[PDB]
Image (tube, rainbow, N blue to C red; front, side, top):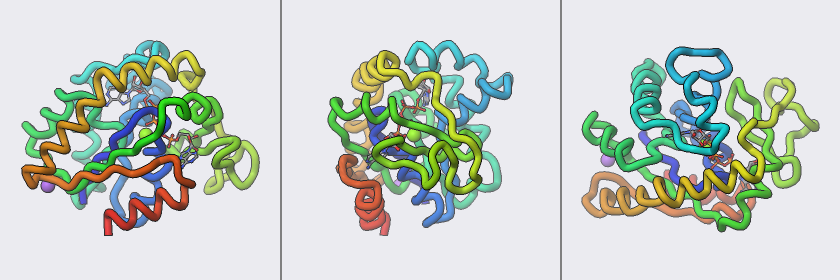
Amino acid sequence: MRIILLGAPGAGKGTQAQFIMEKYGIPQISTGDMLRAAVKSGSELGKQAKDIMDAGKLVTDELVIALVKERIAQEDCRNGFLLDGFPRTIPQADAMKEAGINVDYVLEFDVPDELIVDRIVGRRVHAPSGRVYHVKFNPPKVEGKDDVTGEELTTRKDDQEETVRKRLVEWHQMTAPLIGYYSKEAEAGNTKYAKVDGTKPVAEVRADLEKILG
Ligand SMILES: Nc1ncnc2c1ncn2[C@@H]1O[C@H](COP(=O)(O)OP(=O)(O)OP(=O)(O)OP(=O)(O)OP(=O)(O)OC[C@H]2O[C@@H](n3cnc4c(N)ncnc43)[C@H](O)[C@@H]2O)[C@@H](O)[C@H]1O
Ligand SMILES: [Mg+2]
Ligand code: NA
């Protein structure tokens, strides 16, 4: 199975990706996680993203397209994959199409703009896995600790309010058109498209997604 997670910053894509990955046995491909990992390791493919992410801007298409091509070429992706935060622009989506990458589902995560800042300012992450928590809305079992490894959680450099507001502008201008892009693809029979209410509790969004994915 091949799935695209689509949605504004903090809509809950990464959170729900964890369950989808476990349930259907396909790897999570998060361009955000991959770019951040590249910056941390000083990897030649992706380290350039550092200043761009700080500014709250989108990384260039050709850079993220290359990262995705390399990643989904790995053997853990021969049986399907979960694209999380990719594609983020029309050229990224067309690049998939040109590459002949079919998808089964496009899942839109809907949240009001007014919830996004308070979500991301309370976000804590386990960088090695990509697991995500929230100090108020979805805390770990033990404070500041990853539930699975027990390792110390961290705060993303780009998760301050001002940076979030800039990512939100970027999403409305560059990414929002992908709703129509894939809705049109769905009408042509090339994929299914579904929208979920991401304001519900984590467990319920999970249930709604399971109902869609069967
Ligand atoms: N294709 C691409 N092309 C170009 N540039 C790219 C790119 N991909 C990345 N980049 C670059 O990387 C930068 C960062 O992008 P990115 O890594 O995608 O971060 P983002 O813009 O902040 O949005 P996310 O996708 O990480 O949020 P999310 O939908 O996964 O929500 P989450 O589960 O975390 O949840 C949010 C918070 O709310 C909590 N929460 C989750 N669900 C719920 C719920 N139901 N109820 C209450 N709280 C919840 C969570 O615990 C969490 O704390 C970009 O600016 C760009 O420069
Ligand atoms: Mg994500
Ligand atoms: Na398809």
